[PDB]
Image (tube, helix red, strand yellow):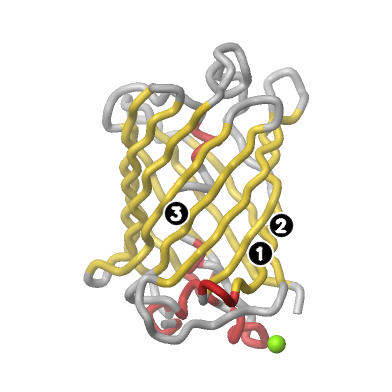
Amino acid sequence: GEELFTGVVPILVELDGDVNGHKFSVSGEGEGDATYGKLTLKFICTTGKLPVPWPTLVTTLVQCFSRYPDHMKQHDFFKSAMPEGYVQERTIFFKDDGNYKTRAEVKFEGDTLVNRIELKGIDFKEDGNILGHKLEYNYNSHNVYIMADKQKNGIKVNFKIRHNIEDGSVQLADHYQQNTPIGDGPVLLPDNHYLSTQSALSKDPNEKRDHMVLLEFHTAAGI
Ligand SMILES: [Mg+2]
């Protein structure tokens, strides 16, 4: 699977969402260079205005582009499942507010890495930080904790995202994640480790549609 990632790979992302009954779609395009753990993508809301803040969708919108150091490469589940791919499922609990449930299939279509997602959000507060659009347009750096889930030939992942609030406070988003292979071939089941992440959000000055431009780095560590 790793041999598929030694150069620059085109990426496509397609999401359909429903948050408290607000339906929307997002399309993204860009490229990944796993040698450097690097992603660059632009996302557009194709149905109009996004009903939630862009930062809340970053984690949902391709961990196969992480840089695994050579001494840890036997622990890279994500690339080992390729090209047939993996199912990535999450529950994201926004503290004092609602939750997202997501199901994604990540796989190659030809030479392009595709991430196709369905997202469902329930129990959000109309005047909370999500539906109230009180989150700053920025993004923090995190540690993503990974363990083997041998009963499903996959992995279990957990981490805390910190979203800055416009009043100086922080909105926590606790992430619970599971990944299972789509194919029935062998995968790399890892020892406990983590991914170190950093991300920068920006806007395309000429773009009038609701959108997000993102630069992200993901690097494995801990063994
Ligand atoms: Mg071991």
Quadrant containing the N terminus in the rendered view: bottom left
What is the C-alpha distance between the residues marked 1 and 3?
A: 18 Å
Q: Earlier in the sequence, mark 1 or mark 3?
A: 3
Residue at x 59% of width, y 86% of height: 74
Q: Residue at x 57, y 55 (%)?
A: 177
- The residue lying furthest to the front in this view is 151
Category of crowding for the residue at label 3, using alpha-carbon neighbours closer than 10 angstroms: few (below 14), some (14–19), many (at least 20): some
| Quarter of the image with the C terminus in it | bottom right
What residue would you read off at disc 3?
40
> Which residue corresponds to mark 1?
195
Tags 1 and 2 in contact by the CB under 8 Å rule? yes
Instruction: Kindly report the distance in space between the C-alpha atoms of the residues bearing marks 2 and 3.
Output: 20 Å
Dot 2 corresponds to which residue?
A: 143
In which image quadrant can residue 207 be found?
A: top left
As helix, strand or loop, the secondary structure at mark 1 comes to strand
Outermost residue to the top: 127
Residue type for callout 1 = Leu
Q: Amino acid at mark 2?
A: Asn
Sequence-first disc among 1 and 2: 2
Q: Nearer the viewer, residue 121 or 61?
A: 121
Q: Position of residue 221 (x, y in %)?
A: 71, 72
Measured Cα–Cα span from mark 1 to mark 2? 6 Å
Q: Secondary structure at mark 3?
A: strand
200 in relation to 10, above or below: above
**Pick the front one: 20 or 82:** 20
Compare residues 149 and 31 and report the one nearer the observer.
Answer: 149
